[PDB]
Amino acid sequence: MDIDPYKEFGATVELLSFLPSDFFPSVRDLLDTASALYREALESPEHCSPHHTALRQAILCWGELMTLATWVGVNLEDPASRDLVVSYVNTNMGLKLRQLLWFHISCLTFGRETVIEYLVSFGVWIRTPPAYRPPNAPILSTLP
Amino acid sequence: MDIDPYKEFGATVELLSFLPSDFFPSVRDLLDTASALYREALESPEHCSPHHTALRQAILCWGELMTLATWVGVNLEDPASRDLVVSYVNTNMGLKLRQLLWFHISCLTFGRETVIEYLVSFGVWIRTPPAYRPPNAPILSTLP
Amino acid sequence: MDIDPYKEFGATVELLSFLPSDFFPSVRDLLDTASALYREALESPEHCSPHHTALRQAILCWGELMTLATWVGVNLEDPASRDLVVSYVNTNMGLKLRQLLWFHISCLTFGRETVIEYLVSFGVWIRTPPAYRPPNAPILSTLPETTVVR
Amino acid sequence: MDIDPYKEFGATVELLSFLPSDFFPSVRDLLDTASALYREALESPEHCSPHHTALRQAILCWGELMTLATWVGVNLEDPASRDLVVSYVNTNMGLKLRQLLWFHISCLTFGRETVIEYLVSFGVWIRTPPAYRPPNAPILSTL
Image (cartoon, rainbow over all chains, first blue to last red; front, side):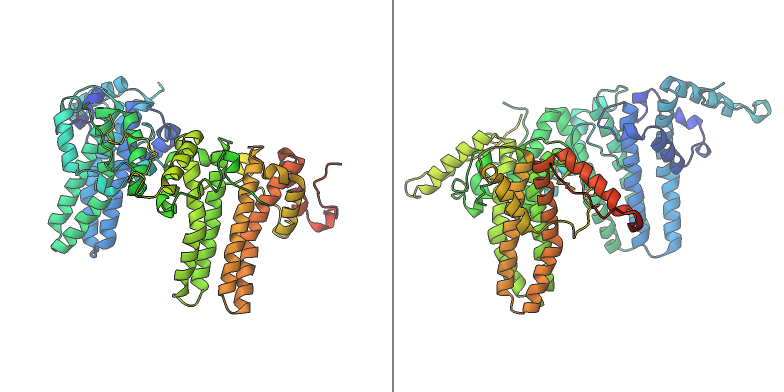
């Protein structure tokens, strides 16, 4: 099928392409954020939110992928092979999981509408040529 | 983070491993079942149900896994090494995805509670001696 | 001290004396059944029922017996006598444990009264010669004989 | 499963680890006490209490372990072996069984809460260095 994991949440894979690949934090950083803020809800027996559901599934997907790649490397012989293997992973699958984790953790921390408006505004900012681009990029905050 | 993908629905990996691995259908068959029965709701922009959410996420996960496995198989030279990697991915991740897709499809089809009762009943059945159990294996049916 | 582990639950050993050994699932099968159906309640800090209590005690007993028998088979110094050791175990203690675990898991799934009636009827059946009894034993199941769930 | 036989009775294997292993009486003594005090209730057709249930099960388990170890010592030839076997038994399985029997008998006799508090206090006593450790170890008593 051709499923978009975001249009169920009011976005698309092309609205999140407004943000470059350089923008998304590491999976370690995002998993730490989750474990810090929504651990007792992700480990809960409740349908607390579609965002929680999707975050659980994404974490399990990252687990499966890491396990596969690690077993591959451990069973593979050459080191450079392993190196560009994990490079391809971090480039293709890690990026998608980063986008997903960011989207969901931000929709939990700030709000779905807030995050979508942030995406629009950051697209404005990053389309704006640098000569006319302010330095104070848009950012998500519960503060002034 | 010690996440169970089934306890927000009322199940557990212990309750799904309570059935033989040789019971869950092929992931191809399950994906076809989904494409036939709920494609219009999985490709929809609606929180139709947590089952739909998890099903979308699981389909995407399987897609990513297959992409990676195909990539590493193409990279590898030996069909022996390819057999190794495909057998591993099947045995572990394909089995997990089989369990997940079966759970969610069967739930959307028959009922979460019917599926859980079916799990326990089929487990007790397959663990019971044949001379002291009903001879026909249990099965789910929408037909009276 | 002349204790019957079932007299408290309304049964006896003379009532389960009729059930054959081929009737009870393996100990691993029964332990898995318990882990899947009542693990949350057996690992709980509550008195859920005497059946839960006795199930916990029986699982602990089986663990102790397993440790003992494995240590023995290991330190025996002849891989030929471990066969007879495990034979004795699976013939006496494994059988008692299967009996007990089955009784409790069943009195939890179905009712205590249901299980006792099943035992009475199964005794009627197994005491009857094959030439005069029906060929298919009575059945205790959460399913109809057709086994189709809707 | 990770069943704790005392969690439903308000204790744990960490609370009874305070008491040493040389503290618990012999299974003979414990069974004599159990008979004398609660025979007509353990031989009874009643869920008189979960303590009674667990005590019955423990007595049966001990009888079973003894049957097994007896059969093993018989079919074994070397007396050194046989003594090593029964020593292993007395050190692991007999120890756990008499922990359980002590817990449940003492509970039936004095109160589950009395016994929990006794465990805590005995921990205090056994952790107290000997220069300040009273010789009068804590003891369960009604009068």
